[PDB]
Every structure is written in structure tokens, then in C-alpha cells.
Image: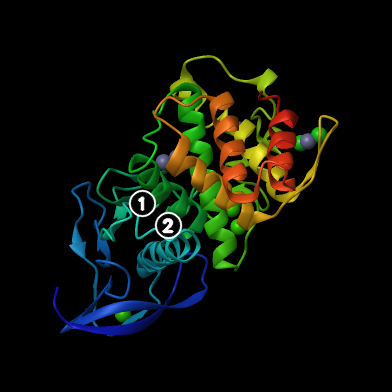
Amino acid sequence: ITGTSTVGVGRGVLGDQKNINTTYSTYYYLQDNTRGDGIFTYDAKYRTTLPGSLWADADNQFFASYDAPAVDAHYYAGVTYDYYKNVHNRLSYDGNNAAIRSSVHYSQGYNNAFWNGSEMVYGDGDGQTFIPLSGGIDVVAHELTHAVTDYTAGLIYQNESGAINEAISDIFGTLVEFYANKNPDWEIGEDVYTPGISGDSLRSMSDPAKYGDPDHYSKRYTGTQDNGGVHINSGIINKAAYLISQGGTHYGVSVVGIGRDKLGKIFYRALTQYLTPTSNFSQLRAAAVQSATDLYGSTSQEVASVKQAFDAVGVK
Ligand SMILES: [Ca+2]
Ligand SMILES: [Ca+2]
Ligand SMILES: [Ca+2]
Ligand SMILES: [Ca+2]
Ligand SMILES: [Cl-]
Ligand SMILES: [Cl-]
Ligand code: NA
Ligand SMILES: [Zn+2]
Ligand SMILES: [Zn+2]
Ligand SMILES: [Zn+2]
């Protein structure tokens, strides 16, 4: 809609307060005109038709429980935009400032969130397995990063390519969570998963095995479930990335950590310059080594640590 750019206030899914960019025209709409061609957030009102209605609020205050998932989808879409813009000079998911549209209250008891090719879609969860999924900034950014992948490398969603696809989304999901600088960690989905249970998550990048995922190529899953293990074998690459950033000794191989910003630069370059739709783990290693070489030099610590990390998780 046309209207005046305004700033509202509300509380997200975890009960934290935040200001949000809105547009005023009789009602205050979740439309943020300050980022690219706009961030728009929609109410699907428990249906499955998309996008639903552009979210309208009478008073620019979003403290109702029903408002929480809209506040977070809207705000975290903004943070994800700022991360790609400020850190990588990428304008929105497509690099051309495309509108970011999200729908919340999709369906009922729906334990999932997804990028559908055109927009973000968030279930509210069933209240046991999940609370509303837009409450997890890593989930928001993980899924928007699938759009970035589709507009770049076009990694296939099956087998080792598909596991790299998943890991890219966990890596940038986590780097956005650190960028937002409120409650970051190397777990995925900890904010929205299992409200009954403290301190768990869907998966861990620092210790994939904590949740049953492989942390070494010799443990790779080779069945056909989960599209050839895309959420499973991602642990191998997630661990390599965790090691590159933070360092550690993993199966006796020592990795010198180089920090988050350099991890992000190296993988973002690998994703946008070097990976192809069918890149496998070994080709990802080569892409990462080449990216680090381009950015830091073939004799740099950064290249040496990329190699140590991939060695540690058994990917040659
Ligand atoms: Ca209100
Ligand atoms: Ca966190
Ligand atoms: Ca997390
Ligand atoms: Ca939990
Ligand atoms: Cl470990
Ligand atoms: Cl270990
Ligand atoms: Na698991
Ligand atoms: Zn997804
Ligand atoms: Zn994913
Ligand atoms: Zn280890």
C-alpha cells in the first residue's frame, strides 16, 4: 500500500520488545519501506492460501500474543536483509532488492517454516514440538538463505549437494543470528524448538553428534530418507565451518580458528563464485580453498585453516 513510513513497537515470540517499520494508511501495516523494494508481512489467518492479508494493526502497537509471530517474521526479515547488505553487499535474496514477503499463522499446528520460491511461510507449531517458527532468527535466515542459494549456485536438494545446500543455510542462519547480536550460538532452532525442554535444538554445528548427525565423512548417511540425508549429512559441513571459525581439535586434528567474519566471506564467495548445482563435499572443499586463496593468499593462515577443517571432518 501507499502511505507514510512509521515506526511501531511490539513483542516477538520470545516476549522481547522491538521496534518495527510500518506503513500508515488508516491502519498500520507490516510494510517496511526502508529496505530494498520493501519487507511485507502477511496474516494467513490459519488458512493455507498465500500470502493472505497484508498485516494491519489499528494502533502501531504489537503486543498481543497473536501479533508475536508477525513481529518476528517482519523484524528478522529486516535483520537478514541488513546482514546480506552490510556484510556481503548483497541486496535482498536475489541481489536486486526483491521484496521480502512472509506469511505467519499458516495452517494450524504446522511444525515447519519454508521459502516457497516467492515468499517465507511460517507455521505456528503445535505448541509441543515448536512454538511459532518465525521466533527463531536462525530459522528465518536459514530459509531465506535457500532463496540466496537458488539465485546463485542452484545447489540441488538431494544427496551431498543437498547437504551442502542445508549447511549453507545453517551457516548463514547462524551468522545472521551472531550479526543480530542478541542470543547467538552454533545450534539451529533453539529458540522455537520444544518449549518444554531447555537447552536442546534441531541440530548442533559445534557437536553434530549430540543430535545423531555425522561429524566426519566416514560416518556419512547413505540411505534415501530425507532426500539422501540432507539434514543429516549437513553436520559434516556444519562442523567444518564451526572449526574454521572457532578452531578446535576434532578427531585429533587441530584447526586454528579464524573467526566468524572470515568464515562468512569465504563461504559466501564459494557459494556465489564457485559452487555449481551438483558440487559434492570434495568440490566444496576446493571451492572454499580457492575462495580463501582469492581473499587472503595461498600462504595465508585462512587457507591453512580451511584445509585443516576439511581434513578434520575427513573431506579431501
Ligand atoms: Ca495493536
Ligand atoms: Ca540462539
Ligand atoms: Ca541458533
Ligand atoms: Ca527446547
Ligand atoms: Cl565433536
Ligand atoms: Cl572430537
Ligand atoms: Na537428529
Ligand atoms: Zn527449509
Ligand atoms: Zn533448509
Ligand atoms: Zn570434535
Which numbered tag is attached to residue 308? none
Q: Secondary structure at mark 1?
A: strand
Q: Residue at x 65, y 46 (%)?
A: 297
Q: Residue at x 71, y 24 (%)?
A: 314
Farthest top residue?
223
Horizontal relation, residue 70 to residue 129: left or right: left
Number of numbered tags placed on the structure image:
2
Residue 283: quadrant of the picture: top right
Which numbered tag is attached to residue 122? 1
Disc 1 marks which amino acid? Tyr
In primary-sequence order, the first of circles 2 and 1 is 1
How would you rate the neighbour count of disc 2 (Cα within 10 Å): few for under 14, some for 14-19, many for 20 or more? Answer: many
Give percent across and percent down for residue 138: 51, 53
Q: Residue at x 45, y 69 (%)?
A: 12
Residue 28 vs residue 298, the one in the foreground: 298
Tell me if residue 196 can be seen. Answer: no
Q: How is the image coloured?
A: rainbow
Which numbered tag is attached to residue 134? 2
Give percent across and percent down for residue 300: 72, 46
